[PDB]
Image (cartoon, rainbow, N blue to C red; front, top):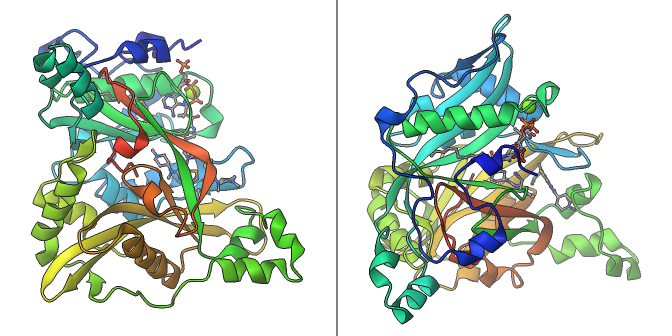
Length: 411
Ligand SMILES: CCCCCCCCCCCCCC(=O)SCCNC(=O)CCNC(=O)[C@H](O)C(C)(C)COP(=O)(O)OP(=O)(O)OC[C@H]1O[C@@H](n2cnc3c(N)ncnc32)[C@H](O)[C@@H]1OP(=O)(O)O
Ligand SMILES: CN1CCC(N(C)c2nc(N(C)CCC#N)c3sccc3n2)CC1
Ligand SMILES: CN1CCC(N(C)c2nc(N(C)CCC#N)c3sccc3n2)CC1
Ligand SMILES: [Mg+2]
């Protein structure tokens, strides 16, 4: 059933995943010296290419590949159109490794055919709370705690094969080469997400959506008008009214995050993320990188009253190409990123996210039910979508956890 994934150090079934008590590696210990120095073999008509994702023109070449060939829905109505500025942000965080950005080109004429990208993350990925209690009940604490320390691992994203090269087994070769390049830097685990079900997720969450421009969402068929609204004289007017928002934020002291906020936003975020079983650890440099405002890419606001920052939220932008329509070419989506509330309820903080995103011309706000995102779904009028996001590890046994015990946002 999985000619590639059955060869890899990942749990092969749910049954297997059910026997997993403790976090730890799946493969035997190996060293950098054990890993092939030479690139993985590839057909003589292709070549490996390492783009420089801080050079405008190489970011542009990867941007076109993804614009034309990255994830689309099954009805081929929407395809992600991550921007060039977003891709430099996402793939060049502090201490990134250029060699973990891996592309395939056709040698003759240099057509770009495939891509995959790794970036560093420091991740808490030790045994989860409910399995540390089982370990205590059995006298097994020391082996449950072995990998408690945050680990410096690889986060994988942006795997893409050009549509003309699909179903030719190119994705496994690009995954093997990325694994080799990561293992040559003495890193042996990765985390990744996907919509598709592969062997074998450690957590899965549904997507949720909050309409901000319901008339446009209906016009492009992201949304339909729900059947009850047909009982009204003007179903669309009622739908618009349902989802209307204030025109300015309600929290006193909301303002954009500045460099001087980085230590306090790091402290409140890290204290909050500590509470989840799987989550990132960020340095001040990574808080700066991932959360300071960047035009068209990431939007972050703090609540400061009387000189103290007590709360913050962030969202990022991923537009999609609207493939069929005549009135619109683009879907402008805001995604809930990290946040922390210490002075107000989470729903009150996230209402201001929706207000600012709507003011800035976003059409929808999306999120997965990770973090404490379930706590504001109903009041803020999010609905579940049909998608999901599955969380995976490479070379790491891990017990199944609920998505409300995951604190890693994947872009
Ligand atoms: C220590 C360091 C480790 C670093 C590496 C960690 C692992 C990272 C793993 C990557 C994490 C990526 C995270 C993201 O970016 S998720 C986003 C993935 N990208 C897209 O969906 C874009 C649109 N689609 C495509 O570009 C292609 O359809 C792709 C490239 C996805 C597959 O190309 P193609 O359709 O031409 O197929 P093939 O003939 O080459 O290959 C077929 C094999 O590929 C397995 N497959 C299909 N889809 C995925 C998928 N999303 N993750 C992992 N494996 C996938 C499939 O089960 C089969 O294996 P098996 O069933 O036969 O066994
Ligand atoms: C009515 N629904 C069907 C379409 C779903 N939706 C908008 C959606 N959008 C997608 N794209 C690319 C636009 C995402 C946004 N916003 C994709 S990609 C794979 C599945 C998928 N589904 C949302 C629920
Ligand atoms: C690694 N990536 C994490 C985020 C994913 N993403 C932005 C995303 N994915 C979605 N899905 C269902 C997972 C797609 C993949 N892979 C959807 S559904 C509707 C909005 C939406 N946005 C795209 C893949
Ligand atoms: Mg292929």
